Structures are given as structure tokens and as C-alpha cells.
Amino acid sequence: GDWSALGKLLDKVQAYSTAGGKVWLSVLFIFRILLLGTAVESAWGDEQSAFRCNTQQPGCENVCYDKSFPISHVRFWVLQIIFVSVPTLLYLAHVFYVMRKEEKLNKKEERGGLLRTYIISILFKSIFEVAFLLIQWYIYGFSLSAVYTCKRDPCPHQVDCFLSRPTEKTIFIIFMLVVSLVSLALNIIELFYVFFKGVKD
Amino acid sequence: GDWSALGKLLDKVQAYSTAGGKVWLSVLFIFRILLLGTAVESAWGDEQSAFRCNTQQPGCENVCYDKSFPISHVRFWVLQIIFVSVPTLLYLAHVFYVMRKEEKLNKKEERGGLLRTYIISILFKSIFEVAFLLIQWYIYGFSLSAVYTCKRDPCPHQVDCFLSRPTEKTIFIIFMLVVSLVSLALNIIELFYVFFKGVKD
Amino acid sequence: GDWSALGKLLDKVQAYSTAGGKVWLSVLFIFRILLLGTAVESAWGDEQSAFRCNTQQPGCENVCYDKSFPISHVRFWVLQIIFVSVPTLLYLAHVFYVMRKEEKLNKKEERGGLLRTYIISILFKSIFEVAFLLIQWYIYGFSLSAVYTCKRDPCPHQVDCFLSRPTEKTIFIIFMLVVSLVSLALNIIELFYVFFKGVKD
Amino acid sequence: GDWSALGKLLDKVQAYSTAGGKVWLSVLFIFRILLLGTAVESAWGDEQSAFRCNTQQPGCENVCYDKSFPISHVRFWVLQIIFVSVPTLLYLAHVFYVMRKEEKLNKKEERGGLLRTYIISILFKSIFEVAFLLIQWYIYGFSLSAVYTCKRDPCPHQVDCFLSRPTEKTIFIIFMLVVSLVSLALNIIELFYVFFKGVKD
Amino acid sequence: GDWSALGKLLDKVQAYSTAGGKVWLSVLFIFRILLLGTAVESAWGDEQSAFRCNTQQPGCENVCYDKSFPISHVRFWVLQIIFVSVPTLLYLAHVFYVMRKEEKLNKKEERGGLLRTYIISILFKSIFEVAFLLIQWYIYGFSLSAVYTCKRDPCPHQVDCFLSRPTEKTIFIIFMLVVSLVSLALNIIELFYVFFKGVKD
Amino acid sequence: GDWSALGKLLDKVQAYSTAGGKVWLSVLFIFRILLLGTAVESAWGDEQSAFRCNTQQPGCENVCYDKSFPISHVRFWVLQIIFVSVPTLLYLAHVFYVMRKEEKLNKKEERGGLLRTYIISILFKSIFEVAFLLIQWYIYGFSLSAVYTCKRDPCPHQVDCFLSRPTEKTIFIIFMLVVSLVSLALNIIELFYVFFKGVKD
Ligand SMILES: CC(C)CCC[C@@H](C)[C@H]1CC[C@H]2[C@@H]3CC=C4C[C@@H](OC(=O)CCC(=O)O)CC[C@]4(C)[C@H]3CC[C@]12C
Ligand SMILES: CC(C)CCC[C@@H](C)[C@H]1CC[C@H]2[C@@H]3CC=C4C[C@@H](OC(=O)CCC(=O)O)CC[C@]4(C)[C@H]3CC[C@]12C
Ligand SMILES: CC(C)CCC[C@@H](C)[C@H]1CC[C@H]2[C@@H]3CC=C4C[C@@H](OC(=O)CCC(=O)O)CC[C@]4(C)[C@H]3CC[C@]12C
Ligand SMILES: CC(C)CCC[C@@H](C)[C@H]1CC[C@H]2[C@@H]3CC=C4C[C@@H](OC(=O)CCC(=O)O)CC[C@]4(C)[C@H]3CC[C@]12C
Ligand SMILES: CC(C)CCC[C@@H](C)[C@H]1CC[C@H]2[C@@H]3CC=C4C[C@@H](OC(=O)CCC(=O)O)CC[C@]4(C)[C@H]3CC[C@]12C
Ligand SMILES: CC(C)CCC[C@@H](C)[C@H]1CC[C@H]2[C@@H]3CC=C4C[C@@H](OC(=O)CCC(=O)O)CC[C@]4(C)[C@H]3CC[C@]12C
């Protein structure tokens, strides 16, 4: 029977949030982490072993693979999720510490103080997710072709290379895209609601 | 001695369900997850290493494997199970939050409100499972042959490829099919019972 | 100090069982699962990598391996153990739920009802284990030879193939066989005892 | 504060044992399991990949490896340790159940009964460990040579094969041998003490 | 309900630290360990398997790889993080032991004593992190080129070698660099604050 | 709230030890185990796969590798740490059992007894660590060269072999050496202190 303080912190951290938004956002986060950890990781098990190019020059395949894939999508998604998860942890730690400070102050002596930080965290999450989506659109796009052309030294003129299981990777990319879009929509809806309620004072 | 609240939530979430259906559905879910995680995963350990085609052109085997298997069945099953498991988690979280809200309201002051969401969750589970079954029937069918014909560029005209342990994969596919059929039958029986009882008011 | 209810359920679920049979069956189950998970799994680490056939035709080894081994014994044993473990879990869940229902009924108001299901579970376990043993006898037998003859297309006429470490696999097969025989004997002894006691009323 | 019953069972199960023998036997068991699980397992990581024979006939190396090593020592040690650990678990379960039965009997009503089983367990442990040691002496001996001669079909006349890191395996075999000898000595000392005390009545 | 002593130790160990610095430093440490353990480790999965040099002499690639990479960056980062984490653990253990000693002393009898050690720990952390950064700058720099020249025996004159995915490794190196810079800035800010407050007495 | 007995045992087992030595020794042990388990294990991931010798005779590389490395350093370090950790566990178990015996004796009835064993454990730890260090100095030394000469049958006259990443292994060997030296110094300081205090009576 030592769950009262945890419940108190949980209910105090959810003051200004919508009744429905909490469950949707939590289950979306859980779905994202489960999908990232369970099966999509094995799809990128063989990123370079099965990658072959049609040439005889040794060492050309390494540089061609480097140029084709500047960074694997799995680690990009990991960075995205950790960067969208950090601000909530910061907010939780800050509110926990200030609550303990207030508890000590009231034990010894037996708007905007919190909403501003909440809005800052929400806008940071939104801007980070939209920036990551824009970067992914700019670098890789949202389609993969099984044939790639490589024109980097020391490979002569042009060479051809083939990827592995492009359809599966494309499907998973689309899934991550739609999940991120849903997350952005939920965050912007929450921000609109809180701002609309704050206008009415 | 901190299990009273968990038991209260567990008994409150099982209000309108049948006496017998709960145990059957729970053990079916446990059997499905155990079978998916324990042994069937190792059967797909070598999906592309042992896959060989009878040709000398480099790079043809990659595209032939891509065309033969647009998506591995294991990850399809993982997506199916997570999509049929999410709505129950949503329902549980929603009922937990509303119960906490009612507890706070009654502490400070010392049909269809829930059945509609229950029916929505049941119908969502049924439609998702039947849609996944229909998609699996449409794409892969329910039989695998050890010999496949590939007619994709840059392979000349037609080439032949061989899979690995098709009989074992076919057996596991049939097992998953019958498990899904049992799940659908249980869900439709529960829906029929609850609707029949609701007709009598 | 929250183990009283678990102990109550444990002692209530063991009403009609013999004093000695409980420990023997439990330790047999633990021994079986430990042996299956600890060391025998590594013996089947290389099932197809070390399997070689004496031919030059590409792709013949895959179909020959498929025909030689329709299904690996490890996954067959996993299916057998899960199918002999499910009915006990069903019985436990059912008795737990009915006990909670009776507790609620008696709180608000401050033979064959269970033996039939017990006998059904025992007979189901016995019939499933004997069926699995019969299937294993019919398909694989209980001996493995290091040399196998393959006569399947597209391999010409007949080819020869060699397995790996047949003696170790044979020893483990014999071990699993004797364990299953002991389990069947214990189950039939329990059934005989309970029926003999029920005859005397 | 729910450790009183566990302590009661622990002190009741250690009635007739020596004051010093308990700690020595327990730490010996812990040392054995830690050594088996931590580092010696990796030494047998490459049992067949690095095993090479000096021939050109395909498939001869498989049968030669099978004949050279009928069973890996690691799994033999696992079987030995599980077979010497089971009887103590049986004794603990039996004494726990009879203690619960006596507790229920005394709640409702508010030598050789145990020593015989104890001696049976001790003698079973001793006979099993000595039998395993004798079998290991009879089959593998206690020395490994880096060169082995194979005279099994279909290899012509005689062929030569080489093992991997024989010195390390020999050292670990000697370590397991001395640990087993210490265990046997401790068990026989305990049996001698208990019999000598029982003679005096 | 056994968390009071842990909370007491946690609040006593955070006496002289800033209100804001605690959460920032803790979340920075958590982010660092999560990034090190989650995804960056897999990027160095193939450090030597994919490393190829353009030559025919056997054994030259080993020495060229040894000369190119005196030590992998992952283990260097592990050493850095463990060396910057040890002093805080030492401080925590020391304060815990002295608090227990004082508790015993006061039970039986029913500035600079701690700040000096705190400052020592802070300066040790700062000097260790700056030393590690300087060493990394001196040895590897902060850029990797896909082509390397090797001039070590027994390779004739000069040979060329190619690395793998240099861009990803460079990105992760930059990430670790900026994280370390942030950590150093936070530590120096904390030291400046505590010294400035100690000047005023 | 069930930590009082554990704290009592912890404070009673630390009677004669120095105030400062406890934390230093504990953190040294934690650092050693963390370093052994975290990163140094992966450095020996490829001990035999990358080891190549300049010859054409099959099977010579196996015996040359066996002669070059009689035993891997990682398992030697594991044996060293387990052998220096066992005596403390023995002392803890013995003091726990005698404390329980005294508690039972005083409940029913409502120098050198411990220091000798403490000194025995300390001297055993010191002698074991110094013996392991001497053995490591005698067998492997403290330096590794990338080129090794092999003169064992059936290799003709002399052959040359190359190791992998010798610099990293040398650095880790030096690290383990200095850690062991620090441990020996701490143990001898503790022994000197306790003997000096015991002289004064
Ligand atoms: C070992 C794990 C399984 C449990 C211990 C860690 C948890 C207490 C932490 C880790 C990650 C946290 C989550 C990280 C991100 C978010 C998104 C966050 O989104 C919001 O709705 C914004 C803040 C709010 O409205 O509460 C809600 C909290 C949540 C689910 C956090 C809840 C608390 C979690 C589960
Ligand atoms: C770490 C794990 C082992 C325990 C912590 C998580 C559990 C509390 C959750 C995770 C998955 C949940 C299950 C996911 C899906 C379902 C199907 C669901 O199906 C129904 O019968 C519909 C709803 C109902 O009638 O209760 C019943 C609840 C159950 C078993 C859930 C029960 C609660 C579970 C076990
Ligand atoms: C995470 C694990 C280690 C603990 C949580 C799960 C256990 C509470 C369950 C899982 C598997 C169950 C076992 C599965 C099969 C059987 C065989 C069954 O056989 C019988 O004797 C028939 C029924 C009876 O007489 O009780 C006895 C119960 C037992 C050991 C079950 C006891 C309860 C177990 C250990
Ligand atoms: C998950 C694990 C770490 C804890 C849960 C299981 C333990 C409660 C069991 C598992 C294995 C058991 C051990 C298996 C074998 C033995 C040898 C046995 O040898 C004897 O001295 C004979 C019997 C006696 O004199 O008590 C003593 C008990 C012991 C250590 C057992 C003690 C209880 C153990 C640790
Ligand atoms: C099994 C794990 C997940 C929990 C058990 C171990 C923790 C109790 C320890 C392990 C590592 C420790 C951390 C290691 C390093 C630091 C940095 C340290 O930096 C400071 O702010 C300096 C000291 C202070 O101001 O408190 C703060 C404590 C913290 C987070 C420690 C807090 C306590 C931790 C989490
Ligand atoms: C699952 C693990 C993380 C916790 C359960 C096991 C611990 C209770 C044991 C396992 C290893 C033990 C350690 C092994 C070796 C030593 C060295 C030993 O060195 C001394 O200072 C000598 C004895 C003393 O002065 O106390 C101190 C105790 C300690 C840290 C032991 C403390 C208790 C430990 C952590």
C-alpha cells in the first residue's frame, strides 16, 4: 500500500489536459514503442550483408552503400522518439521536485506558474516532430526503388546496385508516417483546446 | 495487501461479458502470444539466406525474393495481434480514468454510458480480424509450393527459385488460420448474446 | 503479507488429487520445461547449415531437406507441451472465477459440479499426449540414420544426404519418449484412483 | 514483512544436517551453476564450425564429427546437475506439503517419518553423481588430443581430423571433475555423520 | 510503505545543488545511457567483417585495421561514462554510511564536512570529462574518411583500405561531442554557483 | 517495511572493517564486474574467426591457435573474480547462520570467535589474487605482438600467424592489472590496520 503518492503525482500532472486526449496519446506512444521494438527491427537485420552491386572492383560496394544510405531509418526513428519523449520527462521531474518543495514548506509551517511550461513542452514536441518529418521528406522521400545508380569514386563511371525487400521497408515507412501525423494532429488539437479555454479566462 | 483496487477494476470491466467467454478469450490470447513468441519465430530465422535461384546473373535473386514475398507472415501476424489487442487496452484505460473521476467526485461530495463503447470495441475487433483474414487470403493464399517462377527485371525471361521448409510454414499458417477463426467465432457469439439480452431490455 | 488468497486457491484446486501425485507431476513438468529450454535447443542450432548432399545440381538440397524433415522435433515438442498444459490453466481460471463469484454472492448475503471438469481435463491430457506419441511414432519413428536417400524433383534419380550428430538427437528423442511415458502413467494412475474412489461413493 | 513462513520452512528443512555442511554445499552448488552458465558455455560456441578434416570427399566430416563426439560435455554436465538437484526439490516440496497439512489439522483442532526420506535423497544424490562420473570416465576419459583418426563410412580407409582449443576444454573438464569429487566427499561425510549419530540413538 | 528512508537519503544528498540543475543533469545522464545502449551499439556491429583492403597479401588487412583503429569509440565512450559516474556513487555511499553512523550515535544517546567532498567530486567529474574530450580530439579527431592509406609491415609500400558507413559514425561522434559539451557546461555552472554562494558566506 | 533484518546483518558483518575501506572495496568490485560484463567481452567476440596463418596446409591454423592461446584471458579473469568473491559469501552465510542460531537460543531462554575467520578470509583473498597475478605474468606476460611464430606439427618447419586488435587487448590487460594491484593494496592495508589494532589489544 504505497501507491498514493504516485497516484497524486499522476493526477496533478494531468490538470489542464483533456479528458480524452490522455488515453489516446498514451496508447499511441505505447503502440509506437512496441512496433519499433518488436518486429520492424528484424526487418533491418541484414542492411549491408545482402546489398550487392554489379561490379568487379573491390571496395566500390562500401562507398556506394554509404552514399545510398547516409543513415538508417531505424536509428532516425529512435532519435525522433527519444527527442519527442524527453520534454514530458523534464516536465514530470520539474513538477515532482516543486511538489516536494511545497510539501516541505507546508510541513515546516504546520495563472502561468505551471501552464507556461506545459505549453512550452507541447510546442517543443510539435516543432520537433514536424522538423523530423520535414527532414525525412527532404532526405529519403517516401519511396524506395530496388535499383540504384552509384557514381562515386573509385567506382568507374556508373554502377548499379540492388537493395533488399524494398516493399516491406516502404510499408513500414508509411506506417511510421501515419503514426507521426496522428501524433501531430493530437498535439495540435490539445494546444488549440488549451489556448481556446485560456482565451475565455 | 494492495490488490483490492486492481480486483475492483477487473470485476467492473467484466460487467456485461458472459461468464464463460472471459476465460476462453483470455486463454486464447495467451496461447496465441505464446505460440507466436516461442517457436514459430525461429522457423523464419533463415528467410533469405537459404533462398536460392537457378541463375548466374548477380542481383536477380534479390528482386525475385522481393517479388515472391512482399511481406513476411510473422510481422503480418504481429500487426494483426497488436491491432486486435489495442481496443481492449483503450477500453480499460477509459473505464479506469472515468472510475477515478467518479471516485474523486464522490469523495469531494461526501443505459449506454458504457455498453456503447463495449459494443464499439467488439465490432472493431471483429472487423479488423476479418479484414486481416481476407487480406491474407487475397495476397498469399493458404498454400506454399517449393518451386517459384520469377519473371522480373533484370532477370532474363523466366527463372526458377526454391523456398525452404514449405511444409512447416504451411502447417503454422493453418494453425494461425484456425486460431483466428475461433477468435472470430467467440467474438460474434459474445456480440450476439449481448444484443439478444439488450433486445429484451 | 498478501499470499493468503493464493494459498487458498492453491489448496482448493487440489481437492480430489492424490497426496503424492501433486509433487511428482509438478516436478515432472518443471524437469520437462527445463530440459526443453536449457540445452536441447542448442543441439538443433544448426539444422540446415551443416546438412549437405552429394550432388552438383543447385537447389536440390533444399527440397531434399524439406522431404527428409517435414517438421523439426523441437517445435513438435513445444506444441505437445503447450497442448498438455492448456487444460490445467483453463481449469484453474474457471475455478478462480467461480470462487470469486461465490465470494461475492456470500458477501452480498451476509457431486459433479467440479469433479466432472477435473475428469474431463485429465482425460483430455491423456488423449492428447497419447495422440502426439502415436503421431511421432508414425512419422519419424525413434531412430535416425546418418545417411538418407532423396528421390524428389528436380534431383536426378537418387541422391545421398548426410545429417548431423544423429546420436545426440536419438538420445534426446528417447529421453522425451520416456518422460512422456512417465507422464501418461501418472495421469492414468490418477484417473484410476479417482474413479475407484468415486465407485465406492 | 512476509518472510516468517519462508524462514520457518528453511529452518525446519535443515533439522538433521550438520552446522557446517549447509553453507559448504550451498556455495558449492552456486559456484557450479555460475561456472557452468558464465564462461564455459562460450568455450563450446564453435563445436562444429571450426572442426575440419583433411579430405576432399563431401559429407565425411559430418559422420567423423558424429563418431568423435557422441555427446557434448556441456549438455552432459547440465543433465548431471539437474539430476543431482531434483531430489532436494522433491524433499522440499514434500516437507512443505506435509507441514501445511499438519498446520491445517492443528488449526481445525484448536523416528523415521522424515529422516528416512532424507537418507534416501542423500544416497540417490551420491549414486547419481558417482554413476555420471563413471560414465564420463568410460566414454570420454579425461584427456583430449588435437588429432583424431576417423575410420567410418563413406570415408575411405582412414582420415585425420583436428579439434579446437583442446587445452581449455581439458582444463575445464578437470575443474568439473574436482568439483564433483568435492561434492561426493561432502555428501558421503554428511551420510557418515548422520548414520553415526543414529547408531547412538 | 518502505520508501521513507530512500527519500530521506535522496533529499539529504541534494542539499547544496541548484533547484534546476538536478533534473537537467539526471535527464542528460539517462539520455546518454539510453542512446549508448539502444541503437549506436548496432552501428558498430560490423567493425572488422566489412573492412576490406585492396591487396592480395594475406594478413595485411589485420595489421592495417589495427593501425587504423587503435581503439573502438564505443568502448572509449563506455569508459568515459563509467569514469564520470563513479564519483557520484562514491559520494552517495559515503554520505549513506556517515548518516547511518550518526543515526546509531543518536540512537545510543537518546562548514566543509560535506561540501568539500561535493566540490572534489564535481571537479573530478569536470577534469575527467575534459581530459577524455582532449584525448579524443588528439587521437581520432572528429571526422572520418572512407579511404585510408596503410604503410605498415608486412604490407608492401602503401595499400588502400575502405571503412564502412562513415557518415553515420561521424554523426554519432558529433552527437556524443555535443552531449559531453552540455554536461561540462552544466557542471561548470554548478561549480560557479556553489563557489559564488560560498564566497558570500 | 521489511529491511530491518537486512540492515542488521549488514552492520554486524562490518564490525572490524575500516570506515573508509568498505566503500572503496565495494565500488572497486562494482567497477570490475561492470567493466568485465559491459564492453571488454565484445572485444573477444572474434577470437578465432579473424585469426589467420600464412600457409596452405589444412588444419595447421587450429593447432597453431591452440598453442598460441592456451586459455582466453576473459575466462581467466572470470575465474579470478569468482575465486576472490567466494570467501566473502562464505563469511556472510556463516555469520548469518550463527546469528540466527543465537537469536533462536535467546528466544528460547527469554576475542577470536569471528575475527579469526575474518582474517582467514582476507588472507585467502590476498593469496589468491597474488597467485593469479603471478600465473598471468608467467604464462602470457603483459604484451602482445601482432606476429606469432608457430612450430607445431603437422605444420612444416615454421609458419607465421597474425592476431587481431592487439593494442586494445593490451590496454584492457593493463587496466585489469592496475585494478588487481589496487585491490591487493586495499586488502593488505586492511590487514595491516586490523593486525596493528589487535596488537594493542
Ligand atoms: C520501466 C517502465 C515501463 C516504467 C517506468 C517509467 C515510466 C514511469 C515512464 C517512462 C516513459 C514515460 C512516458 C513517456 C511519454 C509520455 C507521453 C506524455 O504525453 C502527454 O500526454 C503529455 C503530458 C501529460 O499530459 O501528462 C504522457 C506521459 C507519458 C506516457 C510518460 C508516462 C510515464 C512513463 C511511462
Ligand atoms: C507485463 C504483463 C504480463 C502484465 C501487465 C499488462 C496486463 C495488465 C495487460 C497487457 C495485455 C492485456 C490483455 C490484452 C487483451 C485482452 C483481451 C480482452 O478480451 C476481452 O475479453 C474483451 C474485454 C473484456 O471482456 O474484459 C480481455 C483482456 C485482455 C486479456 C487483456 C488483459 C490485461 C493485459 C494482460
Ligand atoms: C512466471 C511463472 C514462473 C509463474 C506464473 C505462472 C504460474 C502461476 C503457472 C504457469 C504454469 C502453471 C503450471 C502448468 C501446469 C501444471 C500441471 C498441473 O497438473 C496437475 O497436477 C493437474 C491439476 C492439479 O491437480 O492441480 C498442476 C499445475 C501446474 C504445475 C501449473 C501450476 C501453475 C503454473 C506454474
Ligand atoms: C529464482 C531462484 C534464484 C530462487 C528461487 C528458487 C530457490 C528457492 C531454489 C531453486 C534451487 C534450489 C536449491 C537446489 C539445491 C540445493 C542443494 C541442497 O543440498 C542440501 O544441503 C540438501 C538438503 C538440505 O540439507 O537442505 C540444499 C538446498 C539447495 C541449495 C536449494 C535451495 C533452494 C533453491 C535455491
Ligand atoms: C537498477 C537501476 C535502474 C537503479 C538502481 C541504481 C540507482 C539507485 C543508481 C545507479 C546509477 C545512479 C546515478 C548515477 C549518476 C548520477 C549523476 C549525479 O549527478 C549529480 O547531480 C551529482 C550529485 C547530486 O547532485 O545528486 C546525480 C545522481 C545520478 C543520476 C545517480 C542516481 C542513482 C542511480 C540511478
Ligand atoms: C542480484 C544482486 C545484484 C544482489 C543480490 C546479491 C548480493 C546481496 C551480493 C552478491 C555479491 C555480493 C558482494 C560480493 C563481494 C563483496 C566484497 C566484500 O569485501 C569486503 O569488504 C569484505 C567483507 C566486508 O568487509 O564486508 C564486501 C561485500 C561484497 C561487496 C558483497 C556484498 C553482497 C553482494 C552484492
Image (cartoon, coloured by chain):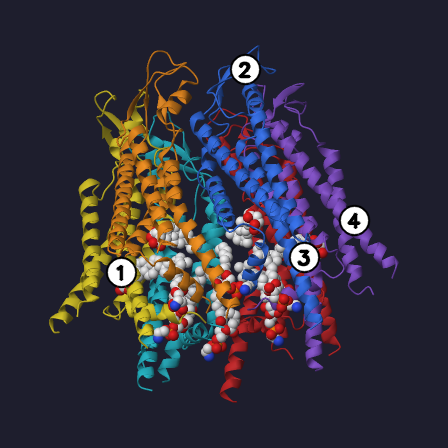
Chain colours: A cyan, B red, C purple, D blue, E yellow, F orange
User: Marks 2 and 3, Cα distance to the nearest angstrom?
Assistant: 53 Å
Tell which residue pokes out farthest to the bottom in this image: B110
Residue contact at pointers 1 and 3, CB within 8 angstroms = no
User: Marks 2 and 4, Cα distance to the nearest angstrom?
Assistant: 54 Å
Residue at image mark 1: E91
Chain identifier of the residue bearing label 3 in the image: C
Mark number, residue C189: 4
Q: Is mark 1 within 8 Å of ligand 5?
A: yes
Q: Is mark 3 within 8 Å of ligand 3?
A: yes
User: Marks 4 and 3, Cα distance to the nearest angstrom?
Assistant: 21 Å
Chain identifier of the residue bearing label 4 in the image: C
Q: Crowdedness of circle 3 by 10 Å Cα count: few (<14), some, many (20+)?
A: some
- Residue D144 vs A63, above or below: the answer is above
- Residue C79 vs C54, above or below: the answer is below
Mark 2 vs mark 4, foreground winner is 4
Residue type at mark 4 is: Ile
Q: Are marks 4 and 3 on the same chain?
A: yes
